[PDB]
Each structure stands twice: as structure tokens, then as C-alpha cells.
Image (cartoon, coloured by chain):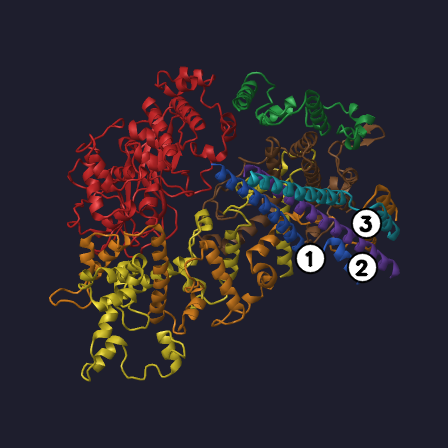
Chain colours: A yellow, B orange, C blue, D purple, E brown, F red, G cyan, H green
């Protein structure tokens, strides 16, 4: 171990001694008597022009770039877990392994939560083996979990209406066309009621329809499905006060 | 006041929730057509506002769906989903971060969670490399890592002529003798003779 | 027209106040960013 | 110990002189901004 | 140390003398005749290994002792600091005779520097994936190639594919580029009436 | 006047060696030998030199050789003439949605190499195809999945006629299940010159860039709008005057003046700035999927469309209603609506009338009124000359 | 006429403010141009 | 304004013509032409300087370039006069001289 560490230290020293004299800045400087280290030809012959190839500061290709930092980080961090473990890096985030280290990925400032949205929707697409439009169709009608159904065209429409006509003053002015509009439809405009949510709210619950509608709105039967206040508040995203 | 045609207004009213019978239920494509009809009637400010709001709604839809359907069984909250996926799904859409910085933050979060053994089974022999012995001081952030690597490659940037690890007592006494606001040639030559 | 030119010269006066406020803020910020001087830290170490 | 104590006093006097000069520099920049501002106020008074 | 302290106290004509005691680009007059060197220190002329084992701790003085070329480069950067602060102290006085002195100092610094490396840079990068770039096999092969380089390995002349394609490239240092940028900015402001 | 004589003269293969003496002095085309000597001779930066010249130097250390979506490839042994091959990528539909880059590199004559990299790989398709404008599959390899972010090289045999005319290679990933085949296509167009005529054309192009300060892609677009084969002429100089005069007259952009000066909406993109087409249509992506200028018919009467994607995209990109879009199209054809193909040649001159309303601070209804009381009542704006 | 004379007297007030701002700037500048005094430099040398 | 603009245009015409036609072969840029002729051809026309100050600046630039041996062949015995031993501190500028 000590001999391999000494070999690695002297390899780094020889590389530093080679590259620190082949600097393109230190060529045309007057009366700085610096010779190259007499192994520059050997370095360029072993590694094909690496000492011949110096890069601009602030580049993607640089050894002090965030791409180099990320490369060293992933190379040293990809071994904390066994490969079959579900907490392994490539298993939990296969996107981060195949990231192309380019200047566009380095400098193109995209907003976060767009990456989160693309990652979640790509994982849902890879899970359910469908397209993005099919994922939105299934998410517009999913009733099993809380905070869902999510009708994305309906949300786009109601946010467009809320941006254009805030507080619904056109409804108050134009009463003869307000006659044609339904009060529950205007409720669905002013606050979020998806069409699937309206179907959930409007259906009646008989003792006959009980076990079927419990499957349709929860999945599992056998009423003890929450067993605790914490699971209920976590399923519906409620506080203890709201619960 | 909606910025569309009265035929578009009639198409919106035809998406009534409860109305006349024998009209069919509004299809998802019908809702998408009404959505792009209202969506084409906005300027760029309202379009960016609507887009940010739709992203901030679809994240809390899709994260709950991913927690329910496809996830390891330990994940039960959005914070646990963040702790798994290493990307924050609760950040509002005003925050911007490039892809390499997101990957850097994700791997740094994974390392800081694996070092405290919060995960399943951390491989203890990998934990004691030199890169992780220097994790707490140098390798945790890009700025200190790049500073250490620059101190390796170009030490000329970091040498000051005043302080140095290992300078002698005569050097320190010279520095005490030399640290004034006024330095004459006679003063510095007497200090050099001393 | 002369009223509008008076407004312009008043705006010039306001800019020349803002420049000095800016220089004072920058000088106090670069004073604050170095807590002790090299000589001040040296005197601390010599007392120790 | 007495010699390095009085060396600490010497470097302290040097640094307090430097801080006095920096404060005078602050005052000079403030007064120069002030005389520019009053000159531009004289200009807008001539326009009025 | 004496030159750095005289620069901080701005005794310029003595600071340049104490820099002449180590570096003179104009040679040295010894017994009336000129000399063939420019560095007044013989372990700076011939690079003497002051410090074997320098990377046991992070010390720029230890690396610059392991090879004194970095001390030589830092001395040149101190000379550039002296010249551009002479130019700045001449420029801040705002008299047209002092502007010629300021342009003289900036021209002297520029002709000490030479030509800025502009077209010799690469701007050339076969962008791999992170999975390709963090290949531990490739990194080990690179270190094995370095060991073959120092053991000279007979240079096997079997022209194979470059398996080290995803290697990051060396970067020129930031401080000299900052000197180049501030020198051309000074001369741009001086070549106008700014 | 001497610069105008330099710009206005035509360069024949006969007049080549004489005009090279008249504009350079020495013959024997290798007179610069380096980027540094060229930039020093013309007082250019490396960035400004990179707008024109992107040689085959330094090929092995990259997988993308195209700079500013163009590439010159001079070949030796052309009877010692050193003919150059300028190839310009044009970035057609689904380029940014399905792949990183897609470059067509010539190896030899009738011997071309397709370099690309699929972004976001699709495991369930496997049927690689490659056609040109939906004519014939050039390359077709069933059971092959291009994995994500990987530089693949595919040999392509292409005729000189097909490459000198503008070709549009179309990368496919069809699935054997009858579901969706992911389309992604880019457009290429090569130009070949002998070395002396190439040097003279590059000389006068760089001199025009130095004189006017206008973009080289912009002068490419205005010379493509009038002529073919890149002949700088007095009509090109007049149109180049008029884009500058409109850009100073109103506060329009360069491409906004281009649309007004009888050019099309530019699809030229860069890593610095996106294309004007994707800025105008797809920067706030409407339903996630992008807009692609397909030749898909759409009747612009306000009730008979039922293709709401392109309709909402056009209405948002032109900031217009259905009725106002219909009367905008009716003004473009003199009060009639023959057929709307949703092509780029219709989106330009649909956008021209909207710009004509907007730069004079008029609504489209006011523009229809003012043209109804003009001597331009039922005239054909689609059939106008540049002078008209 | 009396309005115009009021403008004149206000301009006189502004000039008399500018004169004192000028004297303060000149005094701070001649304070700043000598960093240490002769006695201050003497005391530094005596401490040394 | 027109005269200043015409001077600032004719300098970058005439300097390029002088570099092309009549110059030593080493001169290839405007900075090299400045380094040769010892007068700056890139200065915009707001700057004023008398003829004796221009000649003083030219000879001082020539001396500071010859001392660092940037030129062709500097005569080393002339370099060690007392006037150039006192160049760095006294004789470089007119005020200290």
C-alpha cells in the first residue's frame, strides 16, 4: 500500500513537472529561462498530444471544470452500495450515469423542477410503458390516491381563465350569458374540481354500491386501510389540525 | 375579456359539468382543445405565469402518483421521495440550476446521506478512501475542490512572500522588524543587518 | 421647454449624489470584508 | 518578552495610523461628491 | 518578503531594487561587464529539488520547493504586479504627462508578457457520457501509461486506438489571463480619453 | 467605390486566376496556411472567423465538427486545385426533441458518413431507417436501438446531385408493433467550389461582413432569398440595405426585418441563441410536443379546422384570434382562402401581414380597413415582387 | 421682478454652501496627502 | 467631429498599407508597428501631446525595449553606462531626472 501510494505520488509529480513547463502562456515571455522537462515528447507520444492541448479557462473540457469535479465525484461515489441494492446510484437514477458532459449541459440555465418533472414523468412512462399523453390520460382519471386525479387540460384552462378574468367580473356583468353557465361549472372554474373529481363527488353511495365504490375510490377493501391518524394525514396531505 | 371568439365561448360552455341530457361527456381531447384555445389567448407574461403554475401543480400530482405506484416500499412522503431521488420536487419554479450543478448536488446529497449511514447498507471499506477522508474539508463543495486542485497544479498563485509554513525565527523577527507604515532604505537596511 | 430642462438638470444632481453614496458604500464594504489587517493580526500574535 | 511587547505596540500604532488615513479618504470622497452635487444644483438654479 | 512589504508600503523605487536583487531581465553588470544570466539565485537557475515528498500535505511552498520553476513564475507575477501598480498610480493622477508614464508602464508589462495565447487553445472536446468519463479501468490504464512513461517502456509503436479519449484537458492558470485582461483594458482606456 | 467593384464582380472559373491576382496578388491558394494569419489579415476575432471557416483540422478529438451548423471540407488531388466542400446543416423538424446532433460528413466522392447521437433512447422500436424527404430508405437496419447520448457513425452513399440540391435526411425509429414511429429529420445542402473561386468568394463575403456589421447567416439568407449559388449582386445589396433601414426605422429585430424584406422565417439555430422559428413558435412549448412545419392542410375558416394543435400554435405565435387569423390569410391572397398547407412558405407571408399591421401600430381589422380603402384592395400579397 | 430677485438670493445661498463644501474637501485632501506626520514617523522610528 | 473621425479612419488605413508594402518583414500587426515606430497608431484623437513629449516617449520606449533585449542585437557595452545604471530610478522619467 505504501509503495503504490509512493508510485501514485511520483506519477502525479512527474505529470505536474511535465505540464507546468508546457504552458502556452510561458512561451513568449522575455528572459524566463525555462526549458521543457525533456519528457514532453514522451508525454505527447504516449498521450496523443495531451501536453500539446491546453484548454481555455472556464471550459467544459478543463480539469478544474464542474464536469471534472462531477466525474471524480461519481467515480469515487459509485461504490457505496452493492450493485443490486435499490439505493445504488445507477439503479435509483439511471439518468445521471448517461449525462453528456457538454458545454450546453454545463451552461444552459434551465429551471429546476423542470428536471424533476421530466425525471418523474420519464419514470412513470418507463413504468407503465406508454406515451406522455397516455400518462396524462391515466393521471386525469386515477382515483386511488389522494391529491389525484389531475386533469392537465382542465388545469391549464382554469388557470387561463383565472389569469384573464380574475374574480369572474364578466359573469357579474353579462347576466344573459351568465344564464347559460352552470354554478357548479363556475365553481370548478374558480377552484379546482376536475371532471373525475366531480364524478367522485356527485356519485351516491348506497349500501349495495358500497364495496364496489370502495374498490373504485381506494382499491383494497377491508375498511381498516389507514389504521392511524398519521397514515390518513399523509395520504391526504393534511395537518393534525385539519384532520 | 377572454380574448377568443364567441364560437370558442360556445365551446367552453359546451364543457358544462351538469347541463342538458343527451350531450356527451367532455372528452380529454375536447378538454385539450379548449385548453389550447384559452392558452393561445395570453401574452408572454401570462404564458410564463401559467407555465410555472402548471409545472408546480404537475410535480405534486406526479410525485404522489410515483409514490403510490412505482417506488421502493420505504418511500411514503415527498421528503422521502426527495431523499431517494436526490432532486427536490417541492421547489417552486423561480429557481434555476444547470444540469451539471443538479447532478453535482444529487451526488453530494447521496454522499452526505451515505456517510451518516442513513441508507440501507453502506460499504464501510469504500468509506475510508483519501477522497472521503478529505470530504469534510475539501471535496464537499466545488469551490474548495477546485481551489485544492489549483493549489496542486499552479502553486505560484498561492505563495505569498510574507507567510510560509516552516519559516524560521530569524525570518519572523525580520517580519516584526519590517511591519510598519513607513519603510525607509536606511530602516530596511538596518533590519537586514540585524 | 425650460421647465423640462430644469427637470433634466435636477436628475443630473440626483445622479451625482448617488455616485458618492455608491463610492461610500463600496469603501465601507471593502473595509468590512477585511476584519483585521495584516499588521493588526501580527500585533495580536505578538501580544500572544 | 518586553521587546516583543513593544514591537506589538509599534505595529499597533502603524495600523491605527493606516485606519486614520482610510477614514480621511472616506471623508474626502464624501466632500467631493457633495461639491459636485451643489455644483449641479447651481446649474438647475440657473435654468430656473 | 522585503520586496513584498515595500510594495505594500509603496516604496516603489526601493521595491524595484529589491526585485533587481533576485530577477533582472536586463542582465547583471558584474565588474563592468554584463552577465549571461537573468536570475541571481543559482537554485533558481538550475532547478534544485529542495523538497522530496512535497504532496504529503497541501502546501504550495512545498510544491514550489519540489521544483523552483513555480518560484520563478511567482517572481515574474510579482514583477507584473509591481509594473501594473506603477501604471495604476500613474493613471490615477490624471495629468497628460502622467498618462504617458502610465502607458509606459503598461507597455513595459505587455512587452514583458509577450503574446497572449489565443489560437493555440483547443476549443475541441469529444463529449463523452459520465459513465464513459468516470471509467476506473480507463483511469487505471492512464496511470499504468504514466508508469510506462517514467520507466520508458521502449515506446511499443503499436498504433492502437486512443483509449484515453474522455480525459480532461489541462487548463492554463486564471491569474495570468487576468493580467492579460487587465493590461488590455488599461491600454484600451488609455488609448482613448477615458 | 472600389469596394463596390470588388463586391459586384462575378467570379467565373475562367476569371479565377486573374481575379485572384487582382484581389490578392500571389496565386497558389495556400496563401494564409493558418487561422491566425487569416484573422490577422482581415482583423478578425476567432469568433468572427469561426462564422465563416470551419475546416477539417482537429477532427479526431471531437464527434461534432460543425461550427455554426456548417463545415468546409477541402479535398486534395483534384488535379491540384484543392476543391472545397461547404456543407450547411439546417436543423429541421424534431431535431431538438429526439437527438443531440446529426452531422453528415463526406468521406470521399459519393461516400458520406452519418454522425449523430440519439437523446432519450427508445428501447421498444429497434427499426432504424434513414430516408430523404420520404423518397427511399438510404440506410435501414432493423433490430437496432441507438442508445442514449452515443456518437454513432453510419456510412451513407449519396449522389452528387442529391447532395448539391438540398437534401433532408430523416432518421426513423419505427417499431414492429404498429404504434408510433418517432420521426426526426434534419436538412443538408452542400456547395462545392475550386479553391481560387472559393477564396475570392470568401474574401468578398468577409469584406462585406467587415463593412456592414451584419450577420453572415443573415447575408446567406438574403442571398438565398433572391439568387442561388451565392452570387453577391446589386439586388442583394439593395435588400441588405432595406433590412438595415427597416431595423433602424422600426425597432424590429434582424429576422423581423428579414420577414419584411421578402425572406422566410429563419430556422438557423446556435448554442448562443435559438432559431427565430423555435423562438417564435416553440419556446413556450404549448402541449409539450413541438411545432413542426409539415405540409399538413388546414382550412383557416374559424369553424372547420378540428386540428387544434397547429391552430393554437399559430394563434399564440401570431398573437391573434381565429377570425383575425382568417382575415389575415384572406388579406394574403386578396380576399380569398385557396388552401393553407402549414408550410414555412405559408407561415412566412402569413407573418408578413401581421408584421405589416404591427409595425405601423395597427390592428389587423384596421389593416383590412386601410387596405380596403387603398389601391391595394384585392391585390395578391403572395405574388408580390420585392419592389412591390 | 421680486420673484426673480428671490431666485438670485437663493443662488447666493447655494454658492455659500458650495464654498464651505470646497474648503472641507480641500482640507481633507491635504490631510490625506500626508499619511504620517513628521512627529508620527518619528514616534514609529523610536518604537522601532 | 468629422476631422477626428477621418483621422481615426486614415490611421487604420495607412498603418495596414505600411505594414503590407513598406516595413521590415517582422512587422505583422498594428502592435508590432507601434513597437517599431515608437508612436501609437491606435490612440483616438482626443489625446493631445506636444512634439518634444512625443519624442521623449518614443526614445523612452526604445530604451525600455532595448534594455530587455527584445530587439535584434543590443550592444551590451553601451548598456552599462552610468546613465543606464541610473535609468531605473532617475532617468526613466523627466520629473525625476
Front-most of residues E116 and E9: E9
> What SS does tag 2 mark?
helix
Image coordinates of residue F196 in percent, x first then y, are 40, 21
Image coordinates of residue E13 in percent, x first then y, are 78, 37
Chain assignment, label 2 = C
> What SS does tag 1 mark?
loop
Dot label at residue B178? 3
- The residue carrying mark 2 is C46
Front-most of residues F270 and D12: D12
Chain assignment, label 1 = C
Q: Is residue E13 visible?
A: yes
Q: Is residue F133 visible?
A: no
Q: Is residue H91 above or below residue F301?
A: above
Q: Nearer the viewer, mark 1 or mark 3?
A: 1
F299 sits left or right of E89 in the view: left
- The residue carrying mark 1 is C35
> Residue F83 falls in which quadrant of the image?
top left
The Cα atoms of the two marked residues, 2 and 3, are separated by 14 Å
Q: Are marks 1 and 2 in contact (CB under 8 Å)?
A: no
The Cα atoms of the two marked residues, 1 and 2, are separated by 18 Å
Q: Which sits earlier in the primary sequence, circle 1 or circle 2? A: 1
Q: Residues within 10 Å of mark 2 (few under 14, many from 20)?
A: some
Amino acid at each position: 500500500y505504501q509503495q503504490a501510494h509512493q508510485e501514485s505520488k511520483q506519477n502525479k509529480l512527474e505529470e505536474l513537472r511535465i505540464l507546468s513547463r508546457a504552458n502556452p502562456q510561458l512561451a513568449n515571455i522575455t528572459n524566463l529561462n525555462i526549458t521543457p522537462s525533456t519528457l514532453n515528447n514522451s508525454y505527447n507520444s504516449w498521450f496523443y498530444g495531451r501536453a500539446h492541448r491546453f484548454v481555455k479557462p472556464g471550459s467544459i473540457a478543463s480539469i478544474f471544470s464542474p464536469a471534472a469535479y462531477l466525474t471524480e465525484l461519481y467515480r469515487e461515489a459509485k461504490d457505496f452500495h452493492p450493485d443490486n441494492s435499490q439505493y445504488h446510484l445507477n439503479k435509483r437514477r439511471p439518468d445521471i450515469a448517461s449525462l453528456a458532459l457538454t458545454q450546453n449541459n454545463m451552461d444552459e440555465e434551465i429551471s429546476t423542477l423542470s428536471l424533476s418533472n421530466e425525471l418523474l414523468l420519464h419514470n412513470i412512462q418507463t413504468l407503465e410503458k406508454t406515451d406522455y399523453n397516455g400518462v396524462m390520460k391515466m393521471l386525469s382519471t386515477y382515483r386511488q390516491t389522494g391529491m389525484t386525479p389531475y386533469h392537465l387540460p382542465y388545469e391549464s384552462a382554469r388557470q387561463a381563465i383565472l389569469l384573464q378574468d380574475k374574480n369572474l367580473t364578466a359573469f357579474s356583468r353579462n347576466t344573459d350569458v351568465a344564464e347559460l353557465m352552470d354554478p357548479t361549472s363556475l365553481l370548478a372554474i374558480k377552484t379546482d374540481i376536475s371532471p373525475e373529481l366531480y364524478q367522485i363527488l356527485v356519485e351516491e353511495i348506497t349500501p349495495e354500491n358500497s364495496t364496489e365504490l370502495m374498490k373504485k375510490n381506494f382499491g383494497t377493501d377491508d375498511v381498516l386501510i389507514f389504521k392511524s391518524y398519521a397514515s390518513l394525514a399523509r395520504y391526504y396531505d393534511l395537518s393534525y389540525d385539519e384532520l | 375579456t377572454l380574448g377568443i371568439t364567441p364560437d370558442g365561448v360556445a365551446a367552453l360552455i359546451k364543457l358544462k359539468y351538469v347541463g342538458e341530457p343527451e350531450t356527451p361527456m367532455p372528452t380529454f381531447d375536447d378538454w385539450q382543445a379548449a385548453s389550447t384555445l384559452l392558452q393561445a389567448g395570453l401574452n408572454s407574461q401570462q404564458s410564463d405565469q401559467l407555465q410555472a403554475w402548471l409545472d408546480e401543480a404537475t410535480t405534486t400530482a406526479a410525485s404522489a402518483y410515483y409514490i403510490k405506484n412505482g417506488a421502493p416500499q420505504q418511500i411514503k412522503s415527498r421528503d422521502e421521495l426527495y431523499s431517494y431521488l436526490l432532486i427536490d420536487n417541492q421547489v417552486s419554479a423561480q429557481v434555476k440550476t444547470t444540469r451539471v450543478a443538479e447532478a453535482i448536488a444529487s451526488i453530494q446529497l447521496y454522499v452526505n446521506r451515505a456517510l451518516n449511514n442513513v441508507e440501507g447498507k453502506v460499504s464501510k471499506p469504500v468509506k475510508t478512501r483519501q477522497f472521503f477522508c478529505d470530504w469534510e474539508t475539501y471535496n464537499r463543495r466545488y469551490s474548495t475542490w477546485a481551489g485544492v486542485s489549483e493549489l496542486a497544479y499552479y502553486p505560484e498563485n498561492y505563495i505569498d512572500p510574507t507567510i510560509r509554513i516552516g519559516q524560521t525565527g530569524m525570518m519572523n523577527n525580520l517580519l516584526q522588524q519590517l511591519s510598519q507604515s513607513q519603510l525607509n532604505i536606511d530602516t530596511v537596511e538596518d533590519s537586514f543587518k540585524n | 421647454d425650460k421647465v423640462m430642462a430644469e427637470i433634466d438638470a435636477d436628475k443630473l444632481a440626483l445622479q451625482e449624489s448617488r455616485h458618492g453614496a455608491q463610492s461610500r458604500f463600496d469603501s465601507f464594504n471593502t473595509l468590512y470584508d477585511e476584519d483585521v489587517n495584516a499588521g493588526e493580526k501580527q500585533a495580536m500574535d505578538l501580544y500572544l | 518578552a518586553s521587546a516583543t511587547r513593544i514591537a506589538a505596540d509599534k505595529i499597533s500604532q502603524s495600523e491605527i495610523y493606516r485606519r486614520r488615513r482610510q477614514e480621511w479618504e472616506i471623508q474626502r470622497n464624501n466632500a467631493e461628491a457633495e461639491i459636485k452635487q451643489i455644483d449641479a444644483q447651481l446649474a438647475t438654479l440657473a435654468v430656473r | 518578503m522585503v520586496f513584498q512589504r515595500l510594495l505594500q508600503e509603496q516604496n516603489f523605487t526601493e521595491s524595484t531594487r529589491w526585485l533587481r536583487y533576485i530577477w533582472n531581465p536586463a542582465g547583471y553588470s558584474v565588474q563592468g561587464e554584463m552577465q549571461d544570466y537573468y536570475w541571481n539565485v543559482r537554485p533558481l537557475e538550475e532547478d534544485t529539488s529542495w523538497n522530496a515528498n512535497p504532496l504529503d500535505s497541501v502546501d504550495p511552498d512545498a510544491v514550489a520547493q519540489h521544483d523552483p520553476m513555480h518560484y520563478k513564475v511567482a517572481t515574474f507575477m510579482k514583477m507584473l504586479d509591481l509594473l501594473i501598480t506603477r501604471g495604476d498610480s500613474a493613471y490615477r493622477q490624471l495629468e497628460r504627462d502622467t498618462l504617458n508614464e502610465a502607458k509606459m508602464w503598461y507597455v513595459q508589462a505587455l512587452t514583458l508578457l509577450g503574446d497572449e495565447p489565443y489560437f493555440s487553445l483547443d476549443n475541441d472536446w469529444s463529449e463523452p457520457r459520465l459513465e464513459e468519463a468516470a471509467s476506473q479501468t480507463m483511469r487505471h490504464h492512464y496511470q499504468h501509461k504514466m508508469l510506462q512513461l517514467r520507466q520508458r517502456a521502449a515506446l511499443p509503436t503499436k498504433r492502437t486506438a486512443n483509449s484515453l479519449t474522455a480525459l480532461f484537458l489541462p487548463q492554463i492558470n486564471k491569474k495570468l489571463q487576468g493580467y492579460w485582461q487587465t493590461l488590455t483594458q488599461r491600454l484600451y482606456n488609455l488609448r482613448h480619453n477615458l | 467605390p472600389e469596394l463596390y467593384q470588388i463586391l459586384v464582380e462575378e467570379i467565373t472559373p475562367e476569371n479565377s486566376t486573374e481575379l485572384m491576382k487582382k484581389n490578392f496578388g500571389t496565386d497558389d491558394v495556400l496563401i494564409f496556411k493558418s487561422y491566425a494569419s487569416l484573422a490577422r489579415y482581415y482583423d478578425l476575432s476567432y469568433d468572427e472567423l469561426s462564422l465563416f471557416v470551419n475546416l477539417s483540422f482537429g477532427k479526431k478529438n471531437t464527434n461534432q465538427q460543425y461550427k455554426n451548423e456548417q463545415l468546409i471540407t477541402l479535398v486534395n488531388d483534384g488535379n491540384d486545385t484543392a476543391t472545397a466542400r461547404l456543407i450547411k446543416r439546417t436543423r429541421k423538424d424534431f431535431y431538438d426533441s429526439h437527438l443531440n446532433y446529426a452531422e453528415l460528413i463526406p468521406i470521399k466522392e459519393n461516400e458520406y458518413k452519418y454522425n449523430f447521437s440519439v437523446k432519450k433512447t427508445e428501447p421498444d422500436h429497434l427499426d432504424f431507417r434513414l430516408q430523404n424527404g420520404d423518397k427511399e430508405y438510404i440506410y435501414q437496419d432493423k433490430n437496432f436501438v441507438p442508445i442514449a447520448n452515443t456518437h454513432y457513425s453510419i456510412p451513407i452513399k449519396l449522389t452528387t446531385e442529391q447532395i448539391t440540391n438540398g437534401i433532408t435526411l430523416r432518421l426513423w425509429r419505427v417499431k414492429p408493433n404498429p404504434s408510433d414511429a418517432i420521426n426526426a429529420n434534419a436538412h443538408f445542402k452542400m456547395m462545392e467550389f475550386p479553391g481560387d473561386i472559393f477564396l475570392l468568394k470568401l474574401n468578398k463575403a468577409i469584406r462585406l461582413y467587415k463593412a456592414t456589421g451584419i450577420s453572415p447567416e443573415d447575408i446567406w439568407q438574403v442571398i438565398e432569398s433572391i439568387y442561388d449559388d451565392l452570387t453577391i449582386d446589386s439586388n442583394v445589396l439593395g435588400k441588405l440595405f432595406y433590412v438595415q433601414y427597416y431595423m433602424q426605422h422600426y425597432n424590429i429585430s434582424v429576422s423581423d426585418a428579414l420577414v419584411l424584406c421578402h425572406s422566410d422565417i429563419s430556422q438557423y439555430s446556435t448554442k448562443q441563441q435559438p432559431s427565430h422559428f423555435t423562438m417564435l413558435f416553440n419556446t413556450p412549448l404549448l402541449n409539450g410536443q413541438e411545432f413542426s412545419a409539415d405540409n399538413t392542410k388546414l382550412d383557416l375558416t374559424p369553424g372547420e379546422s378540428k386540428n387544434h394543435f397547429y391552430l393554437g400554435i399559430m394563434k399564440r405565435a401570431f398573437r391573434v384570434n381565429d377570425t383575425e387569423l382568417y382575415t389575415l390569410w384572406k388579406l394574403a391572397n386578396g380576399g380569398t382562402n385557396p388552401e393553407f398547407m402549414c408550410s414555412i412558405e405559408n407561415l412566412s407571408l402569413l407573418y408578413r401581414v401581421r408584421l405589416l399591421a404591427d409595425i405601423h401600430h395597427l390592428t389587423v381589422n384596421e389593416l383590412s380597413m386601410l387596405l380596403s380603402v387603398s389601391p391595394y384592395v384585392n391585390t395578391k400579397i403572395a405574388l408580390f415582387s420585392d419592389t412591390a
